[PDB]
Image (cartoon, rainbow, N blue to C red):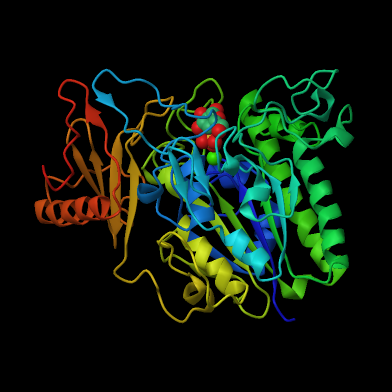
Length: 487
Ligand SMILES: O=S(=O)(O)O[C@@H]1[C@H](O)[C@@H](O)[C@H](O)O[C@@H]1CO
Ligand SMILES: [Ca+2]
């Protein structure tokens, strides 16, 4: 049995610049402030992806990962928590559609749910031992998708409906009182052994993952580990292991705490890489590093710089269709298959992870209930072909997040070659950016290139109708907002 182990190491709310590893053309101030030596170690042994995309919010990205569908299709287009409860902020002008706020599942029977065959279920069915560690956030509370075991994971460390965490601190029981009562729906479950200890949640998850990997080695099976950090999500607890030195770099209390979440996430990566090396698994293990959306840039309560700049040189952040919200740090290591110290700037979307992971696992034939929108990036990894040649990428956010900002709320977009069109459902406004010429999306070229705006509007409208995508409605009329090619 020559099949590789696979680790998908997913960070929460980590931006393109939330690392010491430069994904841009030079080092930023952020690359010089943050410390991720194990990300640099991973890049030295693998391939960096400098144009990797997600959706701008946890739920659409993670539902796209586990089902291999574009967010416009699965309609989980804002964050989930409570059953049958839209998290959208009310708007004066527009109503959000009746979107899939219960999330995803593998089974029929529940309203407002997208049903899809899990790639993790296919891995398990093929004989992989499957481990979930950390943030799940696939289904609302009291829906079958809330439980990682529903997805085909045999082991669950700390995964549930919630896409946040009540506390990073062992001394606060990760959000339980002294009686063990949860302080909120975000309380982190299954870490009772660490309650009352000076163990940061990132460290506890790593220690539990390593226990599960020691078990995995005894089982005589290839393993799949989804190492899904709760870091670096708010609230910004400080990790006292790392905090003092960021204050000496002149960072604010919040920004120094943020840096400590990054460094602890990087220590977790390093601890798993160390385990692979010591256990003799490193030569037959794939590591995929990814983040689920851009760095938080729209909440002055948590972030201290000029708002909407926390992913500079990218514009905006979490919740935005601008690069700051959707462009993610991504690395793939696969010893003897992927060239070490390589870079790939060809674009891809999170749903592409689904067929790629099954291909890595040698699963050449599989049945799914849903169409798979993902396209394998195996040819990018092997440097053989660009599977995204002439490919359009699509985003749909007919929703209202908790914050306003540049490229946030009630919009959809298409990326094709150098060009990105963003359409605002409420106003009919169209922004056109040349991403390589203008990576900060500061120069709207829509008036200068009406033929490009027309071509991309048709592509965007056609795609959204093809996948039965949703749009907001105008409160005044009850009529849906026009598709971009109806303008
Ligand atoms: O899941 S996330 O999408 O990352 O985060 C959700 C949302 O945007 C955040 O504004 C909130 O604070 O936490 C939610 C947890 O689910
Ligand atoms: Ca997130």
